[PDB]
Amino acid sequence: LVISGFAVLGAKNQPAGQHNIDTLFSLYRFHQWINGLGNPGSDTLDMLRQQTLTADRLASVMGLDISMVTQAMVSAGVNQLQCWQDINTVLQWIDVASALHTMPSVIRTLVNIRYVTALNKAESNLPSWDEWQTLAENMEAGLSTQQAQTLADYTAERLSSVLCNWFLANIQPEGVSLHSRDDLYSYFLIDNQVSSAIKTTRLAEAIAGIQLYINRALNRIEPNARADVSTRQFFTDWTVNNRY
Amino acid sequence: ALLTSMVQASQGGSAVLPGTLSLYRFPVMLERTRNLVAQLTQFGTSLL
Amino acid sequence: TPYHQPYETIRQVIMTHDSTLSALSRNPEVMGQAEGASLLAILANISPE
Amino acid sequence: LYNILTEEITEKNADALFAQNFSENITPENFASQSWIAKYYGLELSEVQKYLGMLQNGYSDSTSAYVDNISTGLVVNNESKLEAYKITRVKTDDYDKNINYFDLMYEGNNQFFIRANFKVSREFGATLRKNAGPSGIVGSLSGPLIANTNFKSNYLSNISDSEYKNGVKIYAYRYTSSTSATNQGGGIFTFESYPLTIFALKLNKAIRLCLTSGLSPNELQTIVRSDNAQGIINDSVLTKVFYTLFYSHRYALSFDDAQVLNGSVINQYADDDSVSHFNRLFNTPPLKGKIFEADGNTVSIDPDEEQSTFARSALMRGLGVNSGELYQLGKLAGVLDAQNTITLSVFVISSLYRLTLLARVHQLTVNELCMLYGLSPFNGKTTASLSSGELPRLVIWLYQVTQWLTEAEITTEAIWLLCTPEFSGNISPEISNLLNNLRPSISEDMAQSHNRELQAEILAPFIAATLHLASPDMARYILLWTDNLRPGGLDIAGFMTLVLKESLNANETTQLVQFCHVMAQLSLSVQTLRLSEAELSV
Amino acid sequence: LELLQRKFTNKALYSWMRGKLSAIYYQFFDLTQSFCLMAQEALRRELTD
């Protein structure tokens, strides 16, 4: 470090060689990296003393993947490992990508999404619909089976709420007035407020819906029920036919 | 789990200047230099 | 509404993998490249619309 | 039993073989009844149906025809002999939604279709074969298509006999509107036909093997299908079965995983009450749609590719790797083409999954597996282009090496550094110190001497110092071993001459660093092995 | 620990002692090398080579 004039360590917008707390923190991180490098680390330091350090050499020494290192270097905007600062930035990008089980290119794409107040200035950057779909696929590809199942359940609940609200707001049937989710439940004979955990079969839910419809019609809750039909033998014994 | 390792750097050696001619013959200078280097070796051992 | 389905999927995946943004907190070099509003949209449900 | 299983069956000797293999009071026509087979072989009705499926004899109009196979006998038109045929179906592209059933029926020289529906539509339907190709039209179902109703499809014609084996027979283009149509579900159909006696003999072989081995009938079917086209049983099939059982016992794997490991493809057949292995791997739960192998389209797996394809993402999620590991696996298996594109088929996906399984069962990451393969005697050979007799050798080598590494407490990185041929190519400070300390204590005279023993004795202390060796004798023997190796064409005298140079090194730096690297590798290996000086000398 | 710090041969004594010895060694090496060089010159004169 001293022979090179602290150009190896580098600095963030400051002349190199200064003695403050920030340079001490940088020195601590650099020493930790060198110690963790292992037996060939000394040689690597020599390659860092000159400017002959390459991405492939660093990837092989540290045990990472060449593609991951190259993508991180491209994303971070560094094209040469001149100083320790570039290595630190590359390693930070690699670590963040690994934390999300994804490659650094996806992290760069995620970061590039900015909210810049929707004009009144240069421009606002937002991906298109297809780009959003591709990004969602790439991000979701890193999940396990149980996490995928949990995500599917959450998506089902959110979609159910959104669809119920949209239908209540935009569509009205011919002669029925409905103003709430419970009205939708009573009309379509199927519960939309349930959680995703509970399971059932098609025949069971059809039976439940028809039973609910009969119970509503018999007790004169739904108007204009046919009086003559409601006196059949089957409905007269409804005290015993209402359960399987 | 962390680990640590030794680090080494390139190290150079001393050089030689042109010598000078004394007045005594060879054996006397040989014995004097022998005494001096013996003293130097003792110094090194003490330092270690 | 609005209901951006892929955006919500991305946010849910991010929250599942690393809640509290701790992994993003310890790497200031990459965190400093994101706008505050984008980070808010990551933390709380805020579609572009 | 081995003679029974491995004996060949031909047309001319079928009668003699049947007479030898069965009692004199049992006729081939007795195989026309499933109840008789169940009684004779001591199986339940469901177990028998696992083999033969449902026998077609003119049942009610719909009745379905697959449980999930169909098989029956008919009189050939050529003469008065009865043949027996069996067809198996694999559902695909959202068969559960829509289509109550979808049956392919045979009549002796031509086939037709039977189909019911879930949702009523007014328009007609077109049964295609390929992905909406110009010549993919193979039949048409005339409308209107009301749900829960039988329908027949006009004696499909645009298909060949060769593709009737392992060949899709439907791309159900159903018109929701007058101009809008979609694929509502389909299936891949495989058809076999044999004279009755040969069919009985093959069924006997299969039932005996399955009973004595414990394999499911479909597992044996896919074992024998991946070995040869004719679907016969020979030594290779028995070897694969043994390796399946052995891997299942040793690695505690399921039968499907062991079957894949031995060299077979991923099983896709469904049991009408379970989930196929392929669907369990890649479609539980689906991302948003269903990935199915029947594409053949080239997909790029380049990590640096913008707008990645959904198929690639589904593949990574199935295999449990990221993009870089997928690219490494593609390079290692050799299925990669120019511009980094692969053909989505069962074979390629099976190869990649086999590599992933190999990595997983030995507690190795993908990178570690690549390094070990590089150090292995199989390096330079793509895993896809491996003979049937080489894959077990590779797996046994991997198991033995990993067991030794675990026992000796040596990490994979350490063995890589010990045995790798790659080197940095730059002069290190240790080599610089060695040269600086060695130059004064050397001269050109001993560099030209032909006594390599004397030169080794001269150089031993400095080499010992620069490698942290115990004694000069061990350094001398390491030097002699390296001189025998001749790493970069440099003997001892060449190294001596290279040291005695005033930095006049154009490309000889490569030779010098290679020599030093090999010496360091040897010394480190000896130190790790804790080899005594006497053994090394001897 | 307190007794260790008040020892006669504490850290300070050893540090100063070896520093002084290092300086003495550094100068003595130069003196001895000069002596050896003049001895070599005397030998060269004696052998006329």
Image (spheres, coloured by chain):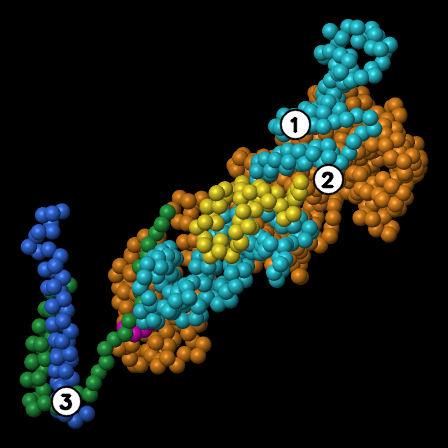
Chain colours: A cyan, B green, C yellow, D orange, E blue
Q: Is residue A117 left or right of residue A57?
A: right
Q: Which mark is residue D232?
A: 2
Could you tell me how far apart the alpha carbons at marks 2 and 3 are, in whole angstroms?
A: 99 Å
Report the amino acid beneath label 3.
Answer: Thr
Pinpoint the chain carrying mark 2: D
> Where D160 falls versus A182 (above or below)?
below
Q: Nearer the viewer, residue A211 or A150?
A: A211
Q: Are marks 2 and 3 in contact (CB under 8 Å)?
A: no
> Mark 1 is on which residue type?
Gln
Q: What whole-number distance in Å separates the C-alpha atoms at marks 3 and 1?
A: 105 Å
- In which quadrant of the rendered view does residue C4 lie? top right
**Residue visible at 50% across and 42% down?**
C19
Left or right placement of residue D215 versus residue D35 in this view: left
Which is in the foreground here, disc 3 or disc 1? 1
The main secondary structure of the magenta stretch is: helix
Specify the label residue B20 is tagged with: 3
- Residue at image position (77%, 34%) is A171
**Magenta-highlighted residues:** D432-437
Residue A60 spot, x, y in % from top left: 47, 59
Label placed on residue A193: 1
Q: Is residue D69 left or right of residue A97?
A: right
Please name the amino acid that badge 2 sits on: Ile
- Per the image, label 2 sits on a secondary structure element best described as loop
Disc 3 crowd rating (10 Å Cα; few below 14, some 14-19, many 20+) is few
Asked which quadrant contains residue D450, the reply is bottom left
Q: Nearer the viewer, mark 2 or mark 3?
A: 3
